[PDB]
Length: 17
Image (cartoon, rainbow, N blue to C red; front, side, top):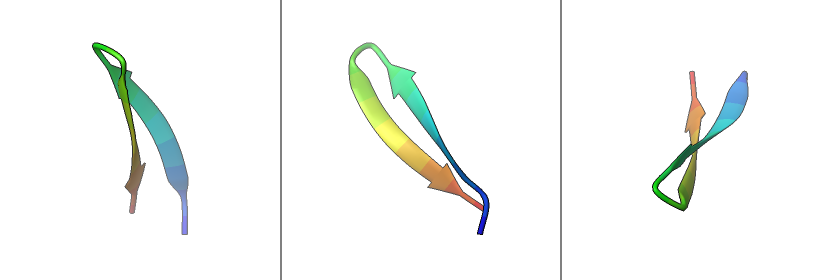
């Protein structure tokens, strides 16, 4: 599962496809 972390305004969330 490819997961990457994205930070938005400090909110760092992880998207996984």
